[PDB]
């Protein structure tokens, strides 16, 4: 069975705010997108990579990546982007992996694929939450504190049988998903977790960038 | 009105996994506990600090901190520790509870939560948006579902309260809480959030130490 990894890299980088769309920021001489793609390939369990980038950077993305990946244009939000990439299509398994998780260890990638090959139809890597999490309303008032031990922070790559992912993305007009496993949960698919990895952290803030720099220079 | 800050520093260090109780880990020449206490005092809005440490390190803590703080022994869990520290108040208008593990917390954040208490909010916690999607997961690693990320916040410290409200909440709790606001919520108190700060991250894993080093050495 073949495994295709889709890499959403079409965001604007508006929150990190380092003056360029995040995927194209050069971390110690390599863009996040190149690093993320290399990690997927180094896992030894990914056969094809499809990267989705801002429409005005498709040429740039090919210049960077060469034959490491197929390049397509992404969309106005992460969900839209994944949907466009999915259009490219049939492999047995599909991974969806944030370019922003550029330092993900290849072994995590392999761990996700192994769980798919173990027969889990949908797989996400998770970590325990360091912070207490609270539900908060629009006025800054706390609604309550869900039990932390019952919650997990979820990373990527998220892995799926291709059939299930396709059906999930095909199927709430006013939602609204922050990851891919959400669509699978929505249509009733069972999602299994595996242990994530601190190194698969998402480069989100300038502190995350500081840490990524310390890791790669270290 | 006086402000006393309670610093839970009595954890075992088992999770951090570097062969020392975490509060006594020396980050670039200063223990997390010394750094955390100095941060509180630097804020200009904390009048008294009470630190709670493992029972066999009370002498060591005093030797380290000197008259920057009163030292007491903590307990078997974080709630127990805070409870023991509260008995020392056997009077201030406000009380902050601050993790020694959030050693790089900016003094301005401490001042921000005190400002809110003085603005009339009886219970105040600093918060940040979530970076990762969060999922509810059962004991078998099966995902139960994904709550809307935008409706949730990661909570930091210092958490601030009117002294009466906190004391009453702990008294009634003494009849698993991962923070102090949760006890206030449990008896019906209302908690307001303020914006936290990425620098007030809790040093929890080895990767966190890597980031702490990059910050203090920068
Ligand atoms: C999938 C998870 O990693 C699971 O925790 C998160 O929910 C992702 O949360 P998020 O807020 O979408 O994180 P971001 O850092 O802003 O973007 C994650 C990845 O989605 C890509 N993304 C962003 C929006 C857009 N119009 N198209 C994209 O393909 C970004 O380039 C980035 O590489
Ligand atoms: C209060 C919050 O920071 C809000 O997000 C978290 O919920 C705290 O979560 P936590 O799992 O208790 O995090 P930890 O890093 O293990 O400990 C937080 C602080 O509580 C202190 N600690 C924990 C156990 C205990 N027996 N005595 C305590 O004084 C630790 O020394 C540490 O300085
Ligand atoms: Cl982005
Ligand atoms: Cl961003
Ligand atoms: Cl600890
Ligand atoms: Cl621990
Ligand atoms: Mg985004
Ligand atoms: Mg603990």
Image: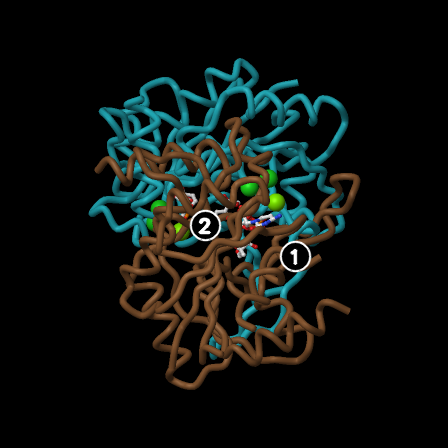
Chain colours: A cyan, B brown
The residue where tag 2 is placed is B100
Compare marks 1 and 2 and give the one earlier in the sequence: 1
**Quarter occupied by residue A107:** top right
Q: Residue A94, which numbered label?
A: none
Q: Chain of mark 2?
A: B
**As drawn, B106 above or below B13:** below
Q: CA distance from mark 1 to mark 2?
A: 16 Å
Q: Using the rendered image of the protein, determine whether residue A175 is visible from the camera's viewpoint.
A: no
Give the x, y percent position of residue B203. Answer: 45, 42
Is B183 situated left or right of B132 in this image? right
Answer left or right for B211 relative to B147.
left
Task: Tell which of B34 and B114 is nearer to you.
Answer: B34
Q: Quadrant of residue A155?
A: top right
Tell which of B159 and B51 is nearer to you: B51
Query: SS at mark 2?
Result: loop
Relative to A70, say whether A67 is above or below: above
Residue position for label 1: B80
**Where does the image place residue B167, in percent across and percent down from the top left?**
60, 74
């Amino acid at each position: 069975g073949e495994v295709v990894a889709i890499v959403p890299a079409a965001g604007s980088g508006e929150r990190l705010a380092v003056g360029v769309p995040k995927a194209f920021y050069q971390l110690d001489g390599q863009t996040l997108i190149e690093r993320a793609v290399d990690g997927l390939l180094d896992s030894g369990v990914v056969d094809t990579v499809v990267v989705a980038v801002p429409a005005d950077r498709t040429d740039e993305a090919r210049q960077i990546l060469g034959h490491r990946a197929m390049i397509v244009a992404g969309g106005s939000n992460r969900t839209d982007t994944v949907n466009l990439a999915l259009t490219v299509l049939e492999p047995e398994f599909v991974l969806v992996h944030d370019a922003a998780r550029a330092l993900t260890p290849p072994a995590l990638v392999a761990r996700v694929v192994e769980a798919l090959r173990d027969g889990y139809a949908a797989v996400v890597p998770v970590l325990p939450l360091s912070d207490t999490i609270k539900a908060v309303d629009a006025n800054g008032v706390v609604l309550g504190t869900p039990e932390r031990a019952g919650l997990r922070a979820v990373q990527t790559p998220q892995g799926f049988t291709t059939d299930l992912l396709l059906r999930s993305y095909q199927r709430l007009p006013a939602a609204e998903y922050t990851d891919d496993a959400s669509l699978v949960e929505h249509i009733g698919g069972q999602v299994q977790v595996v242990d994530g990895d601190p190194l698969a952290f998402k480069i989100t803030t300038k502190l995350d960038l500081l840490l990524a720099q310390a890791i790669v220079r270290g």
